Structure formats: C-alpha cells, structure tokens
Image 1 (cartoon, chains in turn cyan, orange):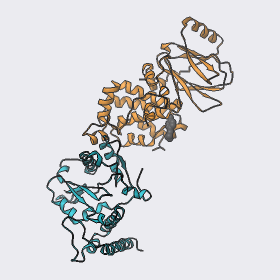
Image 2 (image 1 turned 180 degrees about the vertical axis):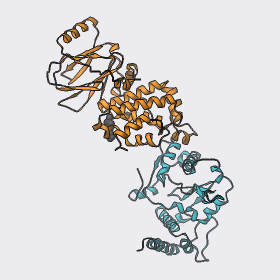
Image 3 (image 1 turned 180 degrees about the horizontal axis):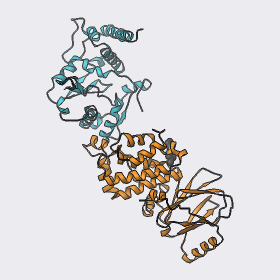
Image 4 (image 1 turned 45 degrees about the horizontal axis):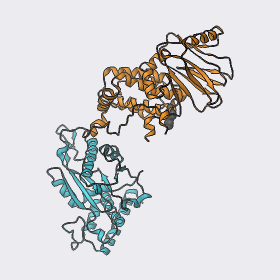
Length: 237
Length: 300
Ligand SMILES: Clc1ccc(C2=CCNCC2)cc1
C-alpha cells in the first residue's frame, strides 16, 4: 500500500523503483499588474524522478512554453508530470522499467495511474513520509540547468555523486535526505555550512563537495544541529 | 389484470410485489396476488420470518406466460414456475378468486411510482443480465455477485451488468488521458451509448434495474452498478438535454421510494455530493437535488 517508516528498507532492496516528486513542476512569481491586481509569471521547472537505490536522477525540465494558453495550470502540471513519467518508462528497456513508482504527493496517484494503464505490473504508490525533495532546486547545479533551459529537456544526474563507492544506498539516501531537509528548513545556513571552507570543492561531474569520510561526519552533524535548530526558533523550545 | 397464484404458504414469510409488501403467517390460507397491472415488469420477493438471511425474488412480465409460486420444502424457498397448459391455469385462478384467497395488487390511481421506477426496464434485457434461459422469469437475491465483482465465483449465478471502470482503457483514449478522465463524455457517449447500450433507454433500463435490485434485495453489486451509472453521466460535460432531464426524474422517484431507515447504507456519500455539488451536472438535477436536501440533508 502506502509507504512509511516501517517498510522503510524496501527502497533499497533489488526491485527497481522510482520516486516522483512534482513540487517544482509549476513555479511562478506572483506580481502586481498596472491595475493593482495580482498576476502570475511562470518560470522553468522540473520533475524530480529518482532511483533511491542507484541515485540516478532523471531530471525532466519543464519549460515555461508548455503552459502557454493552458487553463488550470496546477492541475495540468500533475497530468504533465504523469505524461512525462510514463514516456520515461516507455523509453526504458523492459528489464530497466521499475516495478513500483512512489509519488511524494497523493494527488499524482490518479494522473499517473491513468497514464500507466498500459503497465499493469507496475505499482503506483503513495507515501506517508515528509520527504524534502522539493529542495532539489536549492542545489545550485540543478537550479542552474533548469533556469537556463530554452526548450524541454531531460538531463541525467547521479544525485549521490560517488558516494556508493564508500557507503551503501541506505546511508547515501539518509545523507541525501538530511541534506535536503536542511536546505528546506534554512537554505542560507544550510549552504554556508556546505561551502564555508574554500579548500573543499565540487567536482565538475558532481553536485556536492568532495568530502572525506570524516568531513562528511562533521557536515552531517552540523546539518542535524541546524534542523534541530530551526525547529526551536520555529517552535520556541 | 393478471394473477400470480400460490400453491400454499407453508412458512411465515413477508411477501413483496413491486413496491408493496404484506406479512403472511405460517400455513395461513393464501393463494396469491391478483389484479397485477399488465404492461410493466413486476417483481415478487420474499423474506422468511425465520431466516432474514437471503431476500430473493423473481422478475417477470405477465405478458410472457402463466406464472405461479410453490414452496419447495427441499431447497427451502418459494419458487416461481410457469404453467404451459393455458386452460388448466384459468380454472385454478378462478377457483381461488371465487374463494377470495388472493390479495389485490393495491394500485392507487393517482400513483405512477412503479411506472416511474420501471420506465425503461424490459424483461428481454433483464434476462441477459440474469442468465437462466429455460425460464421466462428471473431469480435474484442478496448474495448474487456481478461480473465485475468476480474479476476482483460461480459464473452461472452472476449478474451480468455492463462493466464500467473509469480507470480503464475502454474508458480512456490514448493521449487523452487527462481529457477523458476529467470529462467522461467520450466514454458515456461513444463507448457506452453508441457502442454498447445503443440508446439512452437501454442505459436507463440497466440503471433502474440496478437500483431496484439493491433496494429490494440488498445486492451490493447492484448498488455499485447504479452508483456507477449515475457518476458517469454526472461526470460528463456533454450529455443530451433530454437525458439530463430524464435522469433527474428517474433519480427523483428512486430517492422518493427508498426506505428512510435504509439510506445510510444504500446511498454512497461521495458519489452524491460529487454529482450534486461538484460535477458538470451540479445544476441539472433540480428535482433530485431538491428532494435529497428536504429528506436527506444529513449525508450532505
Ligand atoms: Cl444494496 C447494498 C448497498 C450497500 C451495501 C454496502 C456495503 C458496504 N458498506 C456500504 C454499504 C450493501 C448492500
């Protein structure tokens, strides 16, 4: 059924699965009209589709042109996510197609499920987890490729950089979520942490700095302090 | 005016005939029902005093044969039967009428409730939904399952209603995924009306049979069917004006005839708030919306 903290290790078994998050698919800048009214201006967005086992990110870029002349954009965006997600699967070789797809927001369930009627053996599933994938746009390299796009485009990343060489997927996902949670709770401080030291650098083919193992431990602690932090500042504890 | 005579009434039973019903006592002298208005299908149904488990019944059209009811003490129910001997049947009925052992089908003459509930129902279509071709009449009971219910287990005893499924391929055109799923006009009009039912009357006929079966017998599949046939209309943006009006009347009489104490189970909350307040046809069911608010504001 749904996905929560009990069946939490299922992500890292050997059934191919993908997470789909639609939070950044439709993005705007609410501004004033000459008449003192309020209007939207759309800016580029992305579908965040992730294999939690391998770290492969299928980042589909959603160009503002897709919205031109359409109505009820919030609802369209969910159908547009589902269409792109189904196209991605269809382009994949059978042996690479996922056996499940877990959506981070329950409103994608029906759009995806309709788009995937042709794939009866693929389970479309919700989750109870509060995953911080929305903060995928606080990752400079990701935000950069999205805002620069002049057309629809799909770009591939490993969101784990090289981590799997040294750690298991379970731990890598936990590092990932910890990092995105911090970006979601206080983006500025989360980023000051990541780049306070100029000797550490982000490899050209990577999204995160190349931290030694001991440096990842110092980073991971500072991120928990922050998340525990902003939880006080916010809850006065 | 036709007659359904009974051999005898050996067990205490509540008897039903279209929307009416009366209590018959163990071996009370009772030999049937007279004065049944020719021209409509009819249903005659049963709820034993002893085993309120299993309501059952028989759909029948008096224009299609001479039918009588006889208790079968082995299988434990009142069974409908046909007499082929046309002249043997007259003499039996006449004898029972002369001894005044029948109840009169009690039609008040201002009342078209039955007509209004059975408008589009036709014995010929009942017999395809309920398959038992050696019999002109059709047995139904509470426990019978539908063809769609068995795909989710005896095929002979099933209700073969028209399968409707909104998250299906029949229902959703390649490349119109969103259009067809938020606006079911394609499925209603092209798939179902033109392709399968042929006309709106056949559709309304299955719709009305579905509700009666649910009302009289408590058949869950029947109810799922009726709700499904309603939702598909109400979720279609392009429906002929004459169907919307017809549907507002049909529903009106169904909701009027429902037992009030039965409404918490027979009516699906989600489907009705959606049809009445959020669907394309939220403004097209004036009489159905009216009665639902005067009489069942609670569900809403
Ligand atoms: Cl006709 C009939 C209508 C509904 C039921 C229900 C079954 C499950 N809970 C909702 C009610 C059973 C029989």
